[PDB]
Length: 75
Length: 76
DNA sequence: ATGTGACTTATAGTCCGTGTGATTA
DNA sequence: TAATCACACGGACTATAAGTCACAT
Image 1: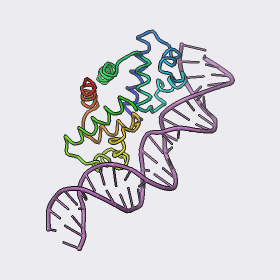
Image 2: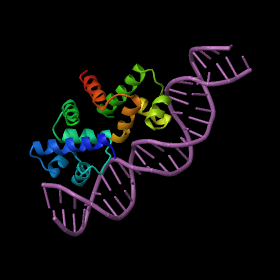
Image 3: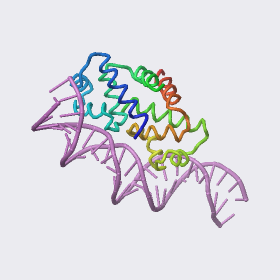
């Protein structure tokens, strides 16, 4: 159980949904399997930084904004 | 290899030194091996979020702090 | 559109070391 | 004498992430 990891996964889901995207959409765009993405959102996967960097590209977001957004999800 | 990995491994090493801690010290406070902290600093090495989370605790800074500094060091 | 258990390969991360170039004596 | 210190790097592990799937929702 990690505080940071479940914030990171909540932030990912949020953005994806804000932007009206599906997992299949985020998957194609980060070049990750869409069942991998589902595992990440359900907080059952401790992704690495390389993986996280592809997700960000996949959300069509900068690293700076994603982290800003993450510090905003941390409250 | 990865952009974000070099920045993350840079900021870790910076803060570490700004608190005059050793790699041995950081390893001990983070519950990682000293040889792994060496690798993270030298070769960037693909940490997980959990292990980043532990290195933030061992550095003794808030998650917010770390990320604010991470942002800055990407902005050239 | 998405959750999940199962699986194999790849690599994250551990634990024993040695060597070099600085100290402090 | 040394004698620690701080780090790079090794070799050989072990633990877990990566990456994928059929079948269900």
